[PDB]
RNA sequence: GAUAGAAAUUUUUAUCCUGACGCUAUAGAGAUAGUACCGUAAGGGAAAGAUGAAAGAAUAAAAUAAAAGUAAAAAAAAGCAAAGAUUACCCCUUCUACCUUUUGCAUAAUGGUUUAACCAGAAAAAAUCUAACAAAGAGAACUUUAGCUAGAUACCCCGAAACCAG
């Protein structure tokens, strides 16, 4: 897979925004995909269960969970139900919040 | 239900013979060999079962296709009866349907 | 990073004696033994249930089945002969360019899209190419010379706004299989064959200048291009004054498959050499 | 246990050994050539490709000869290449 | 020093370089190991899948018992159904009878062939190397030469350095293995020499100590890190590719 | 339904279903009303209109027809000038 | 112990014996010879002239494509007749 | 209707590395053997072996003394044969054998003298669980508007009168 070419202006017309040059001074870290996109995906089970999955997380995952909980708290009025999978490094959030999370992680530079 | 009254000679199995020490050495030939030989090209056994898997019906059908013309008369008949019975049982019998 | 590696120093060595599958990955199998799963084995009591001779699927017991009392109508009549076109959106076309999957410096055709993993074409499933859709016409800021098999009015207008070139060409399934997978074809040791003409049904689509057909009369393109510019209210760029005019004007002969190659050529990939015929009949047949 | 050579080739390999091997080559060459005989009963179709009247599509067609039984009485005369159907 | 680009947010892991030319010729240098291979996540359940896969991907059973159809005889009804006074039977080869077949037995040669996806197998090698390094079971040997062909030399060398009971020696290529090492390890059971292409999960877990040669370490990192940023195979990689010969 | 064929060992399909049903990619099946060509002079204007309308099939019928046809007919198809092309995907379904 | 030599796929061309009765049928077809040329070519030892259709084959190819695939002029005029007829 | 089902066109690198998550005398071939034996004939077709280094160590030696069945040792009011117990086996008190089949069986409805050996749930389209990678997945050929690939979870045994060919 070729590396993304350097652009004079960001974000690109397709919305793609390259990661910040320095690593953010945060405990957890979220690797980019092999296609250079934020690894936030939807997942549906039983036809009525809607979940959002954050993959490829290194470091203190519990820091990521707490930052997600108070980020989505004002939007919902309650702490969202989350699952932490340390053996894999995946945070699972009940509901369709993929678009909101991708913008949130992009601002933090992951 | 009578059991044997004498202790059998204990089998002294050596875990480090030639077979066990070199077991599964070249399983990653494709990954670490520029993808020149798939790991299915190391299987030793029947001609029709090298790198293939299936249930009992698909196995008997596959055997008849490849080595059918090389089988004996009696074996060729027994295979045909096995195919017919499995064909009738799998399609015309069972619980979930 | 992986703080679990610190825990591994204290723990004993990992060997074949202590390995456990992921919990929940292997549901245990239930066998018909014991009081619970016994004396009936989950079949029933008499009838065609316990003896396993219930009727076929869709049989309602003598009554006319649901799938036999509905009158026949043609929903899949001739579906195996209808042409299919994989849609490509300008949102995805912009996405590919920004990430370097494809480059606008070099002309883009169906082959370059496949190598860029943009679209996947299955010639066997009656796919005749890629159609351009106008899903992302508003945010399309690229300048490309793209060649597809079907285009829409808004998709053409969006590309021509930035100063691109759009052309529609027809590919026979025999040729389309070669075009989408060129390397496997070159390993078959066969001469490159001529591209076949579109059938009588598809002649008007590729002959009119409104669709930017490859077989269309070039004299009517400039007046057709200006109609789109007038219709959508965008100033038509003068493409002849750009430094990439040589690249943007590149086309293919109707009997030609690849760029710069000719029918009858044999590509010997092992020796990195190209073979060409010499007989008059061979040259005439591959060029007629 | 399986035969190394398929059963269908046993008769062909019978000709490659023994007295059959010393037979003149010209006789053997004519014997091994199994050319399809001239159609007598069935009526063949000239075109290799045909258009389906129902489907209106180009399809491939092949002539399949109709088996014919030749009684031993025929070998004593000249029936013109035909027999019981 | 690592050649392939190390990710910015992490740093390479380092390990001592040893030599086999002497008992005390240890710690003769320092080598950097790529974090994405030798410092990856400790997946102890992706090793279970690969370890089981290497055991049940070539197993072809050879058990075939004869069902009631394939038994020699029993083609006739033994006695008339009504009036005899005994239980009704239809053949003397049914599974009830003494000499009958098997109603449900192993039928023919059964093949257990299933292929895990390639990225799981590659992930299996990465975690095994990380586990070996994290538990001090990985030693790097420079160029893998031995003073003598006597097999007793390796036994005492491993005893002095506490290399455990079994040691797995690797080399980059088969024809390039030196004669001293080949002759020394050809007479030992717990010590085995395998080319770099013959490395896998089961061999690592079988031997309590893994020894990697410096040329092989660069070979492994080049092959295992290629899958992180690759495309799905349009056609098999044995066929020519633009940048993968 | 032939679960396992005798030539290739795959799963066959029932040609009766495809000749009189249309499967949308959302899982819904489409069919014609029964009796839309029989005795039209007898039926009223409203009744004839009702019989000429396409209708959907409930869950049991939809589930039944999915086990009678193979996986070739469940694929995503992009036909040219397909009237039902816009009905393939479901939208605004709050279940 | 010492491991067995790794299994390697040789890059040399292969040619089965045509006179062997046990050879596979697909290994004597003309398609196999062309595939060897595309694989090796220089080491295949097959004349490059065999890759193009012969004069007998070329006449067959010329007739089949002419009778079944019409010309652009024929297609254009055929549609004009139908358009005039329907109008 | 049940079901039957191609082709055009594609793919396939050689020799060694071969042995066993196959059985161990009701298993595995029927086999110690198509022999005894039953049939005029075609045909059907078995059960059966065990000491030790030496039996040219048979006043010979070692091993479990553990299936049903008997002996050592016949029985003493009263009862689905046992339990609650009791200083005490009974005596006392309390309990309508077991499976199958039925609206309902101690039923006088079915089957079993008892013992050992042998004898009956099998398939992965859709789905749920776990994981890899993710707008893409898969070691070609396909599926894709969070999907694709891999694993795990599944559907028995005995029996007719008959029918056809030699
Ligand atoms: K079934
Ligand atoms: K039960
Ligand atoms: K027997
Ligand atoms: K009775
Ligand atoms: K009864
Ligand atoms: K009973
Ligand atoms: Mg999902
Ligand atoms: Mg169950
Ligand atoms: Mg089961
Ligand atoms: Mg019971
Ligand atoms: Mg019952
Ligand atoms: Mg009933
Ligand atoms: Mg009726
Ligand atoms: Mg497709
Ligand atoms: Mg029989
Ligand atoms: Mg009979
Ligand atoms: Mg019977
Ligand atoms: Mg037996
Ligand atoms: Mg026996
Ligand atoms: Mg036994
Ligand atoms: Mg006893
Ligand atoms: Mg009493
Ligand atoms: Mg009662
Ligand atoms: Mg009653
Ligand atoms: Mg009942
Ligand atoms: Mg009774
Ligand atoms: Mg009764
Ligand atoms: Mg009785
Ligand atoms: Mg499934
Ligand atoms: Mg009849
Ligand atoms: Mg008869």
Image: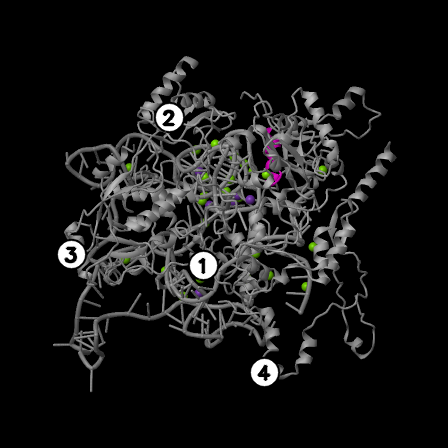
Answer above or below: position of A8 versus D39.
above
Q: CA distance from mark 1 to mark 2?
A: 49 Å
Q: Which mark is residue G9?
A: 1
Chain letter for the residue marked with disc 1 in the picture: G
Image-quadrant location for residue G53: bottom right
Residue at mark 3 shares a chain with residue at mark 4: no
Which residue in the structure is indicated by mark 4?
D18
Q: Are marks 3 and 1 in contact (CB under 8 Å)?
A: no
x, y percent for residue A97 = 45, 21
Which residue in the structure is indicated by mark 3?
E156
Question: Would residue G15 be counted in the magenta stretch?
Answer: no
Question: Is the CB of the residue bearing disc 3 within 8 angstroms of ligand 20?
Answer: no
Q: Answer left or right for G43 relative to G63.
A: left
x, y percent for residue E191 = 24, 56
Q: CA distance from mark 3 to mark 2?
A: 52 Å
* Quarter occupied by the N terminus of chain B: bottom left
- Label 4 sits on a secondary structure element that is helix
Q: Which residues are magenta?
A: F59-74
x, y percent for residue F23 = 64, 33
Which residue shows up at 58% across the image and 42% down it?
C111
- For the residue pair C78 and C88, the one nearer the viewer reads as C88
Q: Which mark is residue C131?
A: none
């Amino acid at each position: 897979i070729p590396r993304p070419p350097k652009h004079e202006h960001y974000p690109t017309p397709s919305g793609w925004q390259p990661p910040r040059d320095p690593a953010p001074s945060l405990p957890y870290f979220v690797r980019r995909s092999r296609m250079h996109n934020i690894p936030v995906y939807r997942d549906i089970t039983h036809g009525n269960r809607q979940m959002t999955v954050i993959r490829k997380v290194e470091g203190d995952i519990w820091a990521l969970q707490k930052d997600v909980e108070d980020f989505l708290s004002p939007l919902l009025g309650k702490t969202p139900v989350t699952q932490v999978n340390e053996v894999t490094g995946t945070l699972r959030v009940k509901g369709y919040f993929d678009q909101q999370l991708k913008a949130w992680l992009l601002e933090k530079g992951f | 239900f009578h059991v044997r009254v004498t202790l059998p000679p204990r089998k002294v199995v050596d875990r480090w013979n030639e077979k066990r020490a070199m077991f599964g050495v070249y399983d990653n030939i494709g990954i670490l060999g520029n993808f020149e030989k798939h790991p299915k090209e190391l299987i030793k056994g029947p001609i029709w079962l090298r790198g293939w898997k299936g249930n009992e019906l698909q196995r008997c059908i596959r055997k008849k296709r490849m080595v059918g013309n090389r089988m004996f008369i009696d074996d060729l008949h027994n295979l045909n009866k096995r195919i017919s019975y499995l064909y009738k049982h799998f399609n015309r019998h069972g619980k979930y349907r | 990073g992986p703080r679990a590696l610190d825990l591994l120093r204290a723990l004993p060595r990992v060997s074949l004696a202590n390995l456990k599958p992921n919990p929940g990955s292997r549901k245990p199998e239930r066998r018909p033994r014991g009081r619970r799963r016994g004396r009936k084995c989950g079949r029933g009591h008499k009838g065609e249930r316990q003896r396993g001779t219930r009727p076929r699927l869709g049989f309602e017991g003598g009554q006319t089945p649901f799938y036999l009392r509905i009158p026949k109508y043609g929903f899949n009549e001739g579906h195996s002969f209808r042409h299919q076109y994989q849609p490509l959106s300008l949102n995805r076309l912009q996405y590919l360019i920004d990430l370097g999957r494809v480059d606008p410096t070099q002309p883009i055709d169906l082959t370059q899209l496949v190598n860029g993993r943009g679209v996947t074409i299955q010639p066997s499933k009656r796919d005749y190419g890629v159609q351009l859709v106008e899903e992302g016409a508003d945010t399309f800021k690229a300048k490309v010379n793209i060649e597809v098999q079907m285009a829409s009015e808004l998709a053409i207008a969006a590309i021509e706004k930035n100063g691109g070139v759009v052309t529609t060409a027809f590919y026979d399934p025999r040729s389309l299989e070669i075009l989408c997978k060129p390397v496997p074809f070159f390993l078959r040791g066969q001469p490159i064959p001529k591209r076949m003409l579109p059938p009588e049904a598809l002649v008007p689509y590729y002959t009119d200048a409104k669709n930017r057909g490859y077989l269309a009369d070039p004299a009517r393109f400039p007046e057709a291009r200006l109609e789109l510019a007038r219709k959508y209210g965008y100033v038509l760029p003068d493409i002849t004054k750009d430094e990439l005019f040589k690249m943007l004007s590149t086309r293919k002969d109707p009997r030609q498959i690849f760029f710069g190659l000719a029918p009858g050529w044999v590509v010997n990939m092992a020796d990195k050499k190209i073979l060409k015929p010499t007989d008059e009949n061979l040259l005439k047949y591959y060029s007629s | 246990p399986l035969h190394k050579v398929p059963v269908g080739l046993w008769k062909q390999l019978r000709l490659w050994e023994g007295i059959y091997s010393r037979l003149p080559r010209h006789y053997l060459r004519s014997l091994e050539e199994a050319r399809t005989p001239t159609p007598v009963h069935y009526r063949p179709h000239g075109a290799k490709f045909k258009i389906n009247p129902k489907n209106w599509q180009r399809e491939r067609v092949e002539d399949v000869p109709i088996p014919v039984h030749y009684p031993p009485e025929s070998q004593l005369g000249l029936w013109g290449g035909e027999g019981w159907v | 020093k690592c050649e392939l680009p190390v990710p910015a947010h992490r740093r390479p892991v380092q390990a001592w370089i040893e030599s086999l030319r002497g008992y005390e010729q240890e710690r003769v240098g320092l080598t950097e190991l790529h974090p994405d291979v030798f410092s990856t996540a400790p997946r102890l359940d992706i090793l279970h899948q690969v370890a089981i896969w290497q055991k049940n991907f070539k197993r072809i059973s050879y058990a075939k018992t004869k069902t009631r159809a394939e038994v020699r005889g029993g083609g006739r009804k033994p006695w008339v159904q009504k009036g005899s006074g005994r239980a009704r039977h239809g053949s003397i080869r049914s599974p009830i009878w003494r000499g009958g077949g098997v109603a449900h037995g192993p039928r023919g040669p059964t093949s257990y062939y299933y292929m895990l996806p390639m990225k799981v197998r590659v992930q299996g090698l990465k975690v095994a190397l990380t586990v070996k390094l994290a538990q001090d079971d990985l030693h790097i040997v420079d160029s893998l030469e031995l003073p003598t062909a006597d097999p007793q030399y390796l036994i005492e060398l491993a005893r002095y350095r506490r290399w455990g009971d079994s040691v797995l020696l690797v080399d980059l290529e088969h024809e390039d293995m030196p004669q001293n090492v080949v002759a020394a390890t050809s007479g030992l059971k717990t010590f085995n020499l395998v080319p770099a292409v013959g490395l896998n999960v089961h061999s690592m877990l079988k031997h309590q100590t893994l020894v990697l040669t410096l040329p092989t370490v660069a070979f492994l990192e080049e092959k295992l890190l290629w899958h992180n940023s690759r495309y799905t195979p349009l056609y098999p990689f044995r066929l020519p590719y633009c940048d993968f010969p | 339904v032939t679960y396992f064929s005798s030539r290739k060992g795959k799963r066959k399909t029932v040609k009766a279903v495809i000749y009189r049903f249309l499967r949308l990619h959302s899982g819904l099946w489409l069919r014609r009303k029964a009796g839309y060509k029989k005795k039209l002079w007898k039926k009223t204007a409203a009744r004839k209109r009702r019989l000429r309308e396409f209708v959907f099939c409930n869950k049991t019928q939809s589930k039944l027809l999915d086990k009678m046809t193979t996986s070739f007919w469940k694929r995503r198809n992009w036909y040219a000038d397909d009237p039902y092309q816009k009905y393939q995907d479901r939208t605004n379904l709050k279940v | 112990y010492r491991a067995r030599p790794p299994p390697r796929r040789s890059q040399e061309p292969r040619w089965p014996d045509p006179d062997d009765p046990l050879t596979p049928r697909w290994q004597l077809s003309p398609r196999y010879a062309a595939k060897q040329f595309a694989r090796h070519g220089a080491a295949s030892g097959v004349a490059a002239g065999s890759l193009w259709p012969s004069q007998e084959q070329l006449r067959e190819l010329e007739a089949e494509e002419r009778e079944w695939y019409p010309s652009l002029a024929a297609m254009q005029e055929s549609l004009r007749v139908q358009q005039l007829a329907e109008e």
